[PDB]
């Protein structure tokens, strides 16, 4: 048959229309990992090799988790309820210096990926050590990934200095351009300078040039805390946004994480440079970083996305919960019950992330021609019934465990709630082994 | 055997110690619905008729959902993303006037109860029409309930005026004191005056007298919105807290819901009168009501509890998610990452609710002599591994679907994730029937 797979579902939320936000009794037709068409089930005349009848479920794009540190799944809830400073100095940094190597990153990324697939995520962004390990795990699992190879001014086990961080990013990009398993381009490598206060101007400019030459996305923290903004004003006499804008670092391919400290000048700079904002509400709350004013940013037409951050400051990788927090918090922050309606929250969590990571041409919404990165959510459960508008249900009363199926590039990674490329029992054993090693070395 | 049931579990979080917040390899012994003892498994010499081996699970008190409207499960996500005023006038109130009767409340409460049990809740507070229907559903399900019979100044189908609302509350209390199925006292009736701006001084004073004479708890909204506080200042020249204090309405048996508008005078009044505060973070965010400063309230030793509110402004009844929101939001609001640590969030969500509803003598913590209201949470799942401190995991990375077992008064209401006194498929059919009736009458 022309189509590999036909999926029938009562509801489809395409995110991009091709003027209601939802389609009733349509089907998706997929071929070679690509969406061929979305059409009414009754009218459809495209035969399919295989057909799946989902019934009372919602099909929508898989989530794009636009900021994370996948391998830190192995530090899940390592040290909760402590100030950023104690958390970092007495727990996270020693644990990183002692435990994080290629094996840690491999097993941690596998664990994260399995959690993410089970909660409907089809693309993750990763900013962490040993990105080749992370990228390789993504390849074996079949999940789409953007690994923002870290760049820092300071030495770690992974690299001694900015130039070495950059070298390894270039090497990793080259390795994935040429990897036998990566012909489909599921894994992209980018540059992940941590933050303006940990990376100097020179490496940042190198990143800009290299990012352009090698077609790589860039991610950086921006205005995460009042402290970082004050520090920048003391040291550079500029807000970080201004510093980055003045050296030409900010542009469309850059995503700026957090942005809890926002003034009108920041917004103008963001509008000018075309950069995206990645919202991480739960992590911002948990660490007391502040309140990203996504309502205000949205009204200013700033591109917005959503990330969970890492499992040591969340502590899960559940985009259903993160998107719900984003939609609820925004109404409180803006004092406006109509701010960030459900369709907008879903859009941030899918197409917004795709745009932020530079991959919206291929994924992030259900449009003919885009990749078949799809999640199916089963609504026939007590906590989801009755349903009046499935779009708002997705955001306000859906558990991630309702995800029944997941496809990436048209490949089934989750079938009736069960992982198809990862072994849950094995991953859990490895997690427990690492916990013991971390707990009592 | 002396004990009816022995439950073995790797972790027990008793909430009240009898100085670590958790017990390793202990067991719970239950007899006649009562906790006989909590002892090390190895040392235990109390035989039991039946023994359950749970392994890597946490036993803790079932949640006390201290404010809700159970039957509004049938309005789940009725009209999302609208301002309080449109929400009420164009959606909720017409739907209530048209659909809410004894049959609505029966089937809605059953649906809510099933959702709540599946997410580990063992006591719910309800403030809604036809409390006898709600109470009767609680009795048949086996869940503990406090039904705060509504009192209002204005006419509804349920009652024409304050005196009639009060009459029906008295009748309902009497009916449950004498109900053949209620000998164990699972169901308590209370008074639920909606808010200072919908109930006059006279009925409020009657409630105080009757509450005392009949040993009934009282629940009221207090300082939910800036509008209500301003309105009270115009009309009475007092903050609502002051109005209620001056007529002697506030006392230990009263729970005050929301409290997003707080000044130092409010706190003093609350400290003086001994009343409890019920925190409903997601509903407050969703409707843009404001930010209850639970960190500040906690530091002032004000008794605190947690509620989900109703399914039209949440939109689920999941106390795992609500407690996590409470713990996270509080750090952001107070700008203090150490504020409302996990053990304190759990305590609010269990013992805090018990105290608020006047039932802490019998439930809310795992102490010898208290009721066996218990939930078991399975940690052997991908998203919960690894685990370093189960207490903080409960709050920061646990899904409600991890609840494997639930007991109320030592009766199993949920066995391996399956309801034992309610039929899930039936409830869902009824929910869909009501949705159709509500959607297209
Ligand atoms: Ca981060
Ligand atoms: Ca989370
Ligand atoms: Ca309410
Ligand atoms: Ca909720």
Image: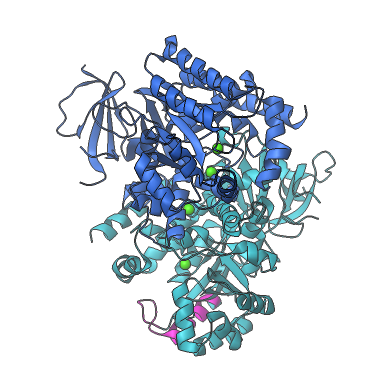
Chain colours: A cyan, B blue
Q: Position of residue B335 (x, y in %)?
A: 43, 62
In the image, B41 versus A165, the foreground residue is B41
For the magenta stretch, what is the residue range?
A: A154-173
Q: Quadrant of the N terminus of chain B?
A: top left
Left or right, A109 with reference to A155: right
Q: Mainly helix, strand or loop, the magenta region?
A: helix
On screen, B50 above or below B225? above
In the image, B387 versus A386, the foreground residue is A386
**Residue at point 49%, 74% (across, down):** A149
On screen, B209 above or below B179? below
On screen, A303 above or below A118? below
In the image, B137 versus A160, the foreground residue is B137
Residue B323 location, quadrant: top left
Is residue A420 visible in the rendered image? The answer is no
Residue B372 location, quadrant: top left
The total of numbered circles placed on residues is 0
Q: Position of residue A166 (x, y in %)?
A: 49, 83
């Amino acid at each position: 048959a022309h189509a590999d797979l036909r999926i029938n579902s009562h509801w489809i939320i395409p995110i991009e229309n091709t003027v209601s936000n939802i389609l009733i009794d349509h089907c998706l037709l997929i071929k070679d990992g690509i969406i061929l068409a979305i059409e009414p089930q009754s009218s459809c005349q495209i035969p399919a090799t295989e057909t799946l009848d989902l019934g009372q479920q919602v099909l929508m794009p898989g989530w794009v988790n636009a900021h994370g540190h996948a391998a830190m799944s192995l530090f899940r809830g390592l040290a909760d309820d402590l100030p950023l400073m104690t958390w970092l100095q007495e727990h996270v940094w020693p644990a990183e210096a002692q435990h994080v190597d290629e094996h840690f990153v491999k097993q941690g990324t596998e664990l994260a990926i399995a959690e993410m697939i089970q909660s409907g995520t089809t693309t993750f962004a990763d900013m962490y050590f040993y990105p080749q390990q992370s990228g390789e795990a993504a390849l074996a699992a079949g999940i789409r990934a953007v690994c923002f190879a870290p760049v820092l001014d300071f030495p770690t086990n992974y690299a001694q200095n900015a130039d070495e961080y950059i070298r390894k990013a270039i090497e990793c990009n080259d390795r994935f351009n040429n990897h036998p398993m990566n012909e489909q381009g599921l894994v992209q490598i980018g540059f992940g300078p941590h933050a303006p206060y940990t990376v100097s101007d020179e490496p940042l400019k190198e990143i800009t040039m290299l990012s352009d030459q090698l077609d790589m996305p860039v991610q950086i923290h921006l205005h995460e805390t009042d402290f970082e903004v004050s520090e920048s004003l003391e040291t550079f006499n500029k807000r970080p946004t201004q510093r980055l804008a003045d050296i030409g670092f900010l542009n469309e391919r850059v995503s700026c994480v957090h942005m809890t400290q926002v003034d009108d000048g920041d917004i103008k700079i963001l509008q000018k440079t075309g950069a995206s904002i990645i919202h991480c509400p739960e992590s911002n709350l948990k660490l007391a970083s502040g309140f990203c004013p996504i309502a205000k940013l949205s009204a200013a037409n700033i591109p917005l996305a959503i990330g969970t951050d890492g499992a040591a400051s969340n502590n899960d990788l559940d985009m259903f919960s993160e998107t719900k927090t984003a939609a609820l918090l925004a109404k409180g922050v803006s004092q406006d019950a109509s701010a960030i309606p459900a369709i907008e929250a879903l859009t941030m969590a899918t197409l917004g992330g795709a745009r932020a990571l530079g991959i919206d041409d291929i994924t992030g919404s259900l449009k003919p021609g885009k990749a078949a990165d799809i999640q199916a959510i089963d609504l026939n459960t007590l906590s989801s019934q009755p349903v009046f508008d499935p779009v708002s249900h997705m955001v306000y009363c859906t558990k991630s465990t309702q995800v029944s199926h997941v496809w990436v590039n048209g490949r089934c990674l989750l079938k009736n709630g069960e992982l198809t490329t990862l072994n849950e029992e094995t991953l859990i054993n490895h997690a427990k082994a690492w916990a013991s090693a971390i707990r009592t070395p």
